[PDB]
Length: 582
Ligand SMILES: [Zn+2]
Ligand SMILES: [Zn+2]
Image 1 (cartoon, rainbow, N blue to C red):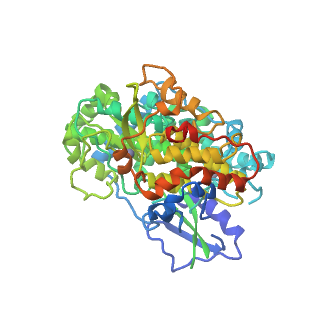
Image 2: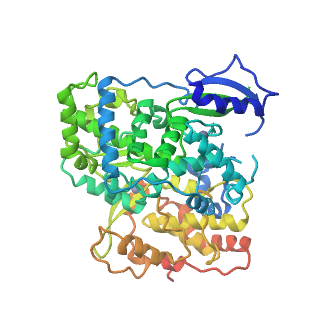
Image 3: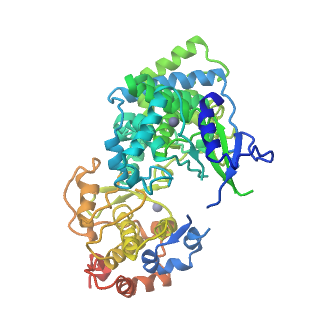
């Protein structure tokens, strides 16, 4: 408690010594409360006018239009201590999993140089605005790095002064850039060196890309076993136990020298003990603490969520296969059985899963998995939208399974080659492309964000009639040489000024390991769509009068946007489609 967090607490006290007060009407039950001080401040979702002017039929679809308008009683809940049998299963599995992940990788520190290059091309590193304006500026000033130095030597000394969380089913904890550096220095290797790649982790999909995920689920489907299970956890980040944070910290067992000590400090001082500032309207800032739940950077959060989810799902597989009988207590011979299962079939069982942070798909040995719930519930990973002891419902068809907000279609090209393509309800895709985040967007910057969405649709969602047409319209309406942008950036092959047919060939044919025949595609007309009825099932407006008038009159919409942007060099991409090709 207060020895590890006191100094952070003491320091904040004094920068608002005029305002400090132990409020007696504080709302916190599960968070330790420490005090309050004076503040007054809040970024809402703005419409992208380039995308909206070129998607007129969707102006009357509430599922699209409502997306642009507008639980903190889950961050204030408490998960119970798992039983001794559960704690043993987790410690054995975590020990084995770090060794497997470490067999072909070397833990290492990430560098000021690496951190600097990141900030100078806009990665979402969840920092705050004070002393310098942006992250770009702090990184060039040696004063910052002296602040970083003071904190760093404090961490070597087992103490913390400035690593404090700022709060804002989504809750995002920003820290100052300095704290973020020290986190990246110690733990950035997990992401920078692809510890959760599929090649390295067998269950993971880190760096795959949406073009690969369907083929990965189809490969899992080829395994002998039961249904495919895709159970979502209710508020994953809020169910991370102190026991989970201690098994995650065992990655430090693979480290040495300075790095080992820097990583141990991040886990001890910032993860297993946290200090947070929260805005309360009654407007004060509350300084609250707790030991458990997830609050790291979003990129370290991804890797440790993937790790702990891989661990949880192997244990659920062990329960289904009868490896242990009860979570109350592991016998000595059950430990040896668990250890032996991991050595004998561990890697095979990892290959039966696709895991992306809190999201999983599991094809177990058989359907005993469906009712194997005691370890999963006791670890605190309670399933969303099903009663605690009701058996899981599995999927019989890999094309039905939800994963990373998508499902996947098998689509046969006119030449017999097989594409496995990503898909989701088209209202969600159009509604997201119609939204920008933040202020001071020029017309040019708004156009270049529209072009990013359009090129993503050409690469990932070409099989949806409405999105191929809208993508071609947006790319016709935005000057041909303007570079696609995004303020928060998986593999993003659409972020390029290269011709999209050349990029399509490189991704779906040349690089595709599932595609044996490498014959390039010569035109967009060779590239197939879903069935017309399947396109409608997934939200197409094909067949509506509104959509027919939009498609027929698209050159008028393209010309409206060109007239707003002004006299620039444009390309007509509409004749790449059969119906505009005269
Ligand atoms: Zn610190
Ligand atoms: Zn679909």
